[PDB]
């Protein structure tokens, strides 16, 4: 019961860390989405970048996926 | 140890012995993180617990074998 | 009204954070969050401090991630 | 079903855990509360004694933060 309650509460914590507006959990995430698009890359680079873009929508205390995805 | 005991007798203090050989971290010098049960104070706090005065004569034993192995 | 909204969310976190992670660390965490604004800090520094604050408000776990974020 | 069984086995680990290792002293509480007053603590020391006393009388044995607070 306590673990279910803790997961519930931490998940509202995740659902209220969306900066209130809910556009993105972290600004860095939405910045990379447009920065990939706003740069003219070849079909070999742009198309792949559009798929490693899906590694985003993660935050530091959650999955460490974005930790190196943002750097890449 | 008897030398320190007699020195404490001369000043009419209470003497103590704490061994530091076999320690390469600060977990037994300082305490432990205050975020869980199992946090344990250092050897100095043991020394104060086992002595009955504000002003003991703390004996640090085997100080020469201190080196950087882990935890700094 | 929106500011009181954000601080009501902070009321939720502070009411549930009792005896979770570090209860003593709660005061340190709040002091560091306040010093984020108090100390004149670069905007990128402010953003990464907010990243670590999101890596806090910890109703996930009392994991070392929370402790390392407090130290950060 | 096998993941549920493994998760329940981890829960069995963490529920059989408390016994040899974790210890609680409900009887000492009153002694710890009283001996604060009759043994004068320094100003910051008295402040942290009052703090650790405040950490009890709300949570005392049912949380990891309360038991480490009682040990402190």
Image (spheres, coloured by chain):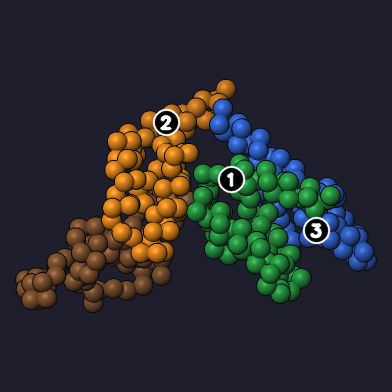
Chain colours: A blue, B brown, C green, D orange
D36 on left or right of D5: left
Residue B46 image position (x, y, % from top left): 25, 59
- Say which quadrant the N terminus of chain A sits in: top right
Q: Chain of mark 2?
A: D
Q: Return the mark for residue C17.
A: 1
Secondary structure state at the residue bearing disc 3 = helix
Q: Nearer the viewer, mark 1 or mark 3?
A: 1
Vertical side of C53 occupied by D13: above or below: above
C12 on left or right of B18: right
Task: Name the outermost residue toward the top.
Answer: D1
* Residue designated by label 2: D15
Q: Nearer the viewer, mark 1 or mark 2?
A: 1
- For residue A15, which quarter of the picture? top right
Q: Residue at x 32, y 40 (%)?
A: D30
Q: Chain of mark 3?
A: A
- Say which quadrant the C terminus of chain A sits in: bottom right
């Amino acid at each position: 019961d306590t673990n279910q309650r803790e997961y519930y509460l931490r998940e509202q914590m995740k659902a209220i860390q969306k900066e209130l507006g809910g556009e993105d959990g972290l600004s860095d995430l939405e910045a990379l989405r447009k920065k990939i698009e706003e740069v003219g890359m070849p079909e070999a680079v742009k198309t792949k970048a559009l798929k490693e873009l899906d590694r985003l929508e993660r935050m530091q205390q959650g999955s460490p996926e974005a930790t190196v995805a943002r750097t890449y | 140890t008897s030398l320190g005991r007699s020195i404490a007798r001369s000043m009419n203090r209470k003497f103590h012995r704490i061994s530091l050989g076999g320690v390469r971290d600060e977990a037994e010098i300082r305490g432990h993180r205050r975020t869980y049960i199992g946090a344990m104070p250092g050897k100095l706090i043991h020394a104060m617990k086992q002595v009955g005065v504000i002003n003991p004569v703390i004996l640090l034993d085997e100080i020469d074998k201190m080196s950087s192995d882990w935890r700094g």
